[PDB]
Image (cartoon, rainbow, N blue to C red):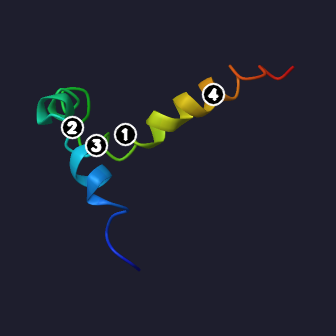
Amino acid sequence: GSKKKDNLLFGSIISAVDPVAVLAVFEEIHINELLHILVFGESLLNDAVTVVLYKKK
């Protein structure tokens, strides 16, 4: 439940950071590729923050 966002600050700015920067993305996604826009944003950092930290000993 609760609100629909965590804080317009990140749901209004980072979510609208220069529409051009957000639109430049619509040039590589066909809707069905707008949802994974968040899943492909982490899998990258998650594998680049843990592997770069201690690269599994």
Query: Are discs 1 and 3 less than 8 Å apart at CB?
Result: no
Please identify, in this view, whether the residue under mark 4 or under mark 1 is nearer the observer: 4
Q: Nearer the viewer, residue 32 or 57?
A: 57
Distance in Å between CA atoms under marks 1 and 3: 14 Å
User: Would you name the residue on which mark 3 appears?
Assistant: 14
| Mark 4 residue crowding within 10 angstroms, few (<14) / some (14–19) / many (20+) | few
Query: Are discs 2 and 3 less than 8 Å apart at CB?
Result: yes
Label drawn at residue 37 = 1
Residue 15 coordinates in the image, percent (x, y): 25, 46
Distance in Å between CA atoms under marks 2 and 4: 24 Å
Residue 51 coordinates in the image, percent (x, y): 70, 23
Residue at image point 78% right, 22% down: 54
> Mark 4 or mark 1, which has the lower sequence index?
1
Residue 34 coordinates in the image, percent (x, y): 30, 43
Query: Are discs 4 and 1 less than 8 Å apart at CB?
Result: no
Give the quarter of the image for residue 19. top left
Q: Nearer the viewer, residue 13 or 19?
A: 13
> Mark 1 or mark 3, which has the lower sequence index?
3
User: Would you name the residue on which mark 4 appears?
Assistant: 49
**Vertically, is 49 above or below 7?**
above
Q: Secondary structure at mark 1?
A: loop
* Residue type beneath disc 3: Ile
* Residue type beneath disc 2: Val
Please identify, in this view, whether the residue under mark 1 or under mark 3 is nearer the observer: 3
User: Would you name the residue on which mark 2 appears?
Assistant: 17
Left or right side of 30 for 33: right
> Mark 3 or mark 4, which has the lower sequence index?
3
Label drawn at residue 10 = none
Residue at image point 19% right, 29% down: 21
Q: Nearer the viewer, residue 18 or 32?
A: 18
Left or right side of 19 for 53: right
Give the quarter of the image for residue 6. bottom left
